[PDB]
Length: 36
DNA sequence: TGGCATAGATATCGCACGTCTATTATCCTCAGCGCAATCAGCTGTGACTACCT
Image (cartoon, rainbow, N blue to C red; front, side, top):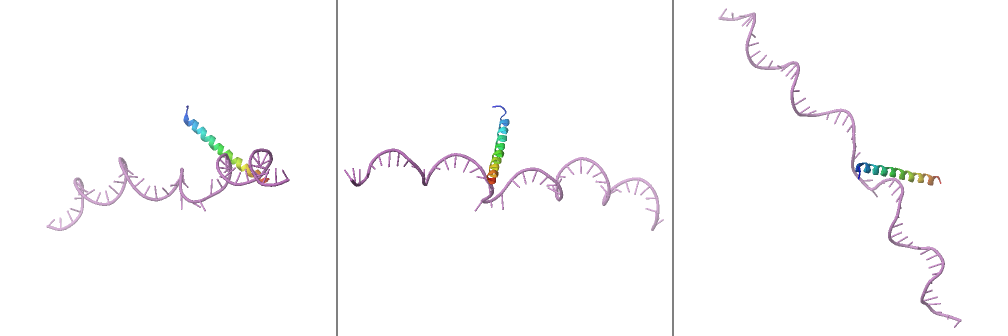
C-alpha cells in the first residue's frame, strides 16, 4: 500500500536469496552424504 | 465333539509430498556502411597584352 515497487524488489531479493541458500543447502547435503 | 464366522493384529500398495540437473536455438560490442552545411578546386568569364595586316 506504500511504494509497491519497493515491496516487489524486496520480494525478488528474498526469492533470489532463498534460491541461492536452498541450492547451497542441497550442495552441502550432497557433500556430507558423499563424505559419509 | 467340530464347521467357521468375526474381529485382533500387520503389514502393503497406492496417492500424495520434498528435491535436481538438464532429448535441446540469448544479450551487449565494435567494425562496416549510410546522411547534411563548409570549403576548396575545376571550369567559365572578363581584364590586360601579343601578333598579322
